[PDB]
Structure formats: structure tokens, C-alpha cells
Image (cartoon, rainbow, N blue to C red; front, side, top):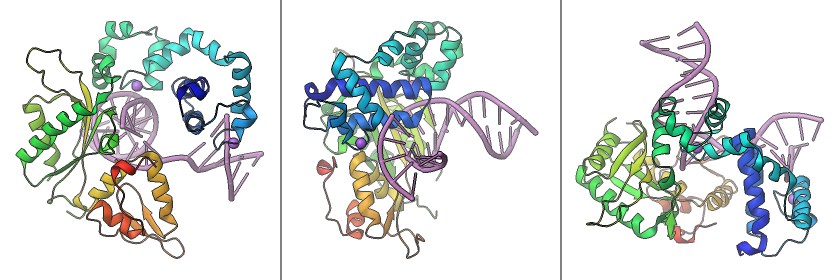
Length: 327
DNA sequence: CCGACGTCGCATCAGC
DNA sequence: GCTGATGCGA
DNA sequence: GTCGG
Ligand code: NA
Ligand code: NA
């Protein structure tokens, strides 16, 4: 379905979503508008009325009403008003800085700090994460062409193997499903020495090596199992330098790795279908394990998993390529 | 009518 | 100083 | 805000 079909409506709903999350701090209303915006974007007909839209799951009385107003007038009074509101639109905007959520954005705007300019003038009020978000504001809102992702992967797989050739690393996200572009890079790392039942050094050494070859440029957060940071392809010769990119790296015990890989490969929709399909066969799959219910409903021990396919086998489902995992 | 609605690792705050 | 809560991102 | 026990 094309944008032209219901884009005005889904744009409206997504904007309303953002104000709920960032200004009203009503996360569930945020998810409500987003789900409605999704089911509408997938709807293969130009919507003619709110009543028509209400047939869709996630679309209730109040959104039907708003769709009516939008159809008859080409706008929404409430949205027009909040757009023009100096406080609210500023709060909503500041949250586009990574590390600035609804609560921090609220406080800044309370003390008069409203713009990137104002943030720039008030560095000492920013935490480390927020400074990095501000520094790379523009870069972080850019997408990553698959070709750059491949080049990023080259470096990541290369430097990981160089640290220890027994590491296993997998770049997941939409990239692994074959997307033409990506929002960031999500890397899953395991090692034969790290299981559930078993150093608190394995992640640090990989981060270190990627910083040594100047791939990783900044650190948002870093513990023993999760790294969140910034990276950058080297500039080719004398050419225009690449944007800085968001990269996450997480260390998962070997026995939970492929549950990890499956889960962080997605898509979101596929994971739920699969996870329902799922319960029906009598098994329980979170991001870590698969476990059998359980005649009353008592989940038993985590089953052995040694590939993605192993999981599919358990629930009598035929292995499916990442490319065929949009749902 | 009224509660559910991803969850969890890390950084930092709030309180002791 | 430590422990638990809160904010944040994904 | 929407769904449903
Ligand atoms: Na509906
Ligand atoms: Na933000």
C-alpha cells in the first residue's frame, strides 16, 4: 500500500503517538496510536470514514472520530493546537536527542532550555550519553545503506576473529533479513567459554580492539554483557567522511545464543506469530530460551538449542530464512 | 468497569 | 559508602 | 486509546 492512500491519517496518528510518549508520558497511549497507524498503513484501500477504519484491530471509537474530523477538514484541531504550543513542541523535539527522554526534555524546557542551541550553551547540564546524542544529532537520524552495513560488518567480523578465532559474531536486525538500509548495527557475540552455568572479560576485549583500529569512536554505555556506542567507517582517501553510526554489541551465553539471534533478527511481527505458534504446540520461547509447558502450565527446563533451526524443529515449524521473516 | 498493554542492562539519581 | 528506584534505549 | 476478562 502506498503513502498516498492513507498517509495523512497515519502521519496524524504517529504524531499523536509522539506527543503522548514525550509530553503526556502515556506510553500505552503511544503504543495504541502506533498500532493503529500500523494496521492502517497495511490497509490496501483509501479509507473513506472513521466507521470503515474502526473495523480494523487497534482502531477504536476515538480514532474513528479523529479520522472523521481529518477526512472532513484535512486537519485535526487538537494536533494543530499542540503543534503551535511552544512548551509541548519543544519538549517533543528535544527527545530526538539520544539520551534525552520525556523526563529530561520536560526539565530542560522547564528551565528555559528549548533548542539544540540551548543544549549547546548548557553542556554542564548534560550527562555523557546526552552530550554524545547532541554531538551526533544529525548523524543519528540518518539511515545506513546496506552497502555501508556490509563494510561495517567486514570490520566487525574481522576484528572479532582477530581477538579470538573462537568468538562467534552475528549482525542481526533488519540487516540480517536483507533490508536495503538500517537504522543502526546490532551485533550478537558469544564464545565457547561463556555459558549460563559457567570471563567477565570477553566483551571488553572486543570493544577494545574495535577502538584500537578506530572503528568505535564513542561509548554510550558498557558493562559485562552489553555495549552501546558509536562507530564510523574510515574515510576513503580524500573523500567526504561517513556519518557516525550507532552500534550495539551484546555478549550472550553460548546456550542462549541462537534464541538471542532469532529474537534480535525479527521482525517484531514475525516474533509474535512465531511465539504464539509457539504456545499452541506447548512451548515457551523468550529472548533467552525455549521451555516446555507443562500440563497445568508449569514451564520446565530450557531445551538444548544449537542453531536457529533447532528452535523451529521444536515447534514443528520448517526453518525459515531471515529474508522471509517480515511476518 | 477496570487492568493489561515488551523487558532488561546500564548510568545515574534518591535515600539511607 | 551501599541499595534500590528511575530514566533511557531498543 | 483499545481490547477484553
Ligand atoms: Na476496531
Ligand atoms: Na531521546
